[PDB]
Image 1 (cartoon, helix red, strand yellow):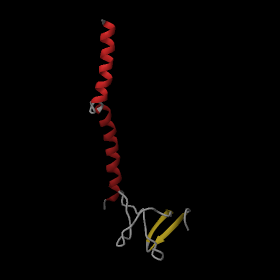
Image 2 (cartoon, each protein chain N blue to C red):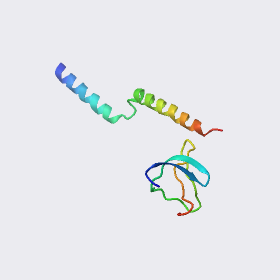
Image 3 (cartoon, rainbow over the protein chains, first blue to last red):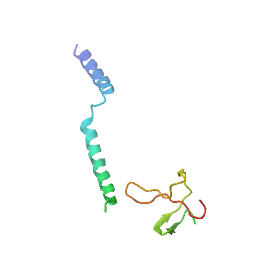
Length: 48
Length: 49
């Protein structure tokens, strides 16, 4: 019984991750913020 | 002179870099091309268009 519950839970984990697209936002936001900072720095070259 | 680091002076626009045959298709009323950081990255040769 414990073996079947464990295997079923792992399979539900992988296809739930495969379905929901907004799962990894904790990582993604980090990347976004860094890129966004660099972006503003570049356009500060175009100010008088 | 192309594919060499040269000092270019195109109609008073001054700079340093490598001139390369491009793939950008200018419209006939345009004579420059700028970057996000306001640096020219495409230019039209005033003698041979």
